[PDB]
Image (tube, rainbow over all chains, first blue to last red; front, side, top):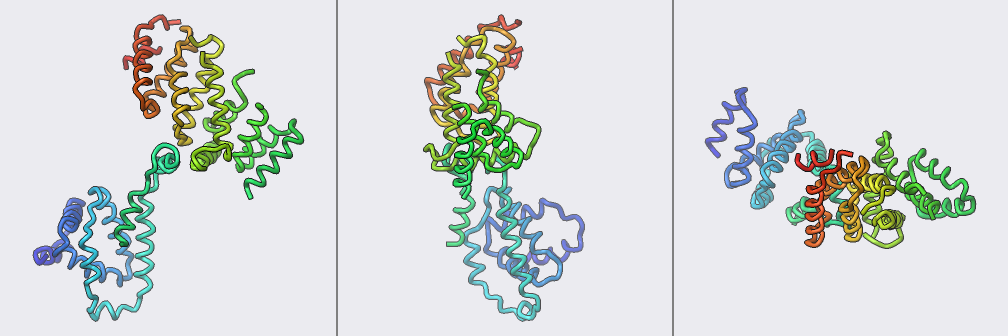
Length: 146
Length: 206
């Protein structure tokens, strides 16, 4: 994580960033949340206090990358996020708090919309006829909630 | 509420059957209560092909895309209504269409080939646009229809082409060995048959 943090300073100003770097970062986070997720959680926490709408875009990109990576979601990262203590004073001094909740709600609402398809409607019509399906994402979400 | 309104309009039309199709036209104009329209055309049919085939084919394959989406949503929603039982008019009209399938099945007649073609295109519209999933009996009678031998006319060529395209598109409806041997023997007959000059074999080869 230290090397990534050190290179982030140079990468922020550089315009050579491409989707390959984001895909590699998402794959690394999904495969190993031991080091990268620890800093990523703090980075996402800091992004929720900004005035610009940057949490929604990052969440949408992460969801798109995860969907393209065949549901590359780390189950052990949830325990690190729950055990992580937001004890910093900069986060507690942020005046705008409802904005983060609104952004999270919008991200959740837009992430569920990725399953909308006319073929998903035909599978929903096939449920009590052909084959009961179009519900794996919901089941996975229930497991994550558990 | 919708069921009671539909039943009330059904009784009103039973009391004045001359205006039943006018009420069905009002239904397709105002673009709600599709079950009422289906039930009215069913009570009206209760020679041509049928008012049912014309009505639902025009609904699913007309220029108006709003009507197409509306009736497709109707078909999808009705399909989930217990997956059986005469409670929904969807299964009533499905049985009526299946009865028509029995009616035109036999060597296919010269007079029934065009009706078979229209019925087959209607079934294509249903299972393709409307998302209908056929039952085992529906699939069986469909396969019985496709594998028929029309009497080598341009209508026969069109019918064979449409049936072949249905098999290529909705190949999930075979799902059995005896229907597999039926369709391969039908394909072999189709290969042997080359007097269709008076564009089917080109499609098969392609």
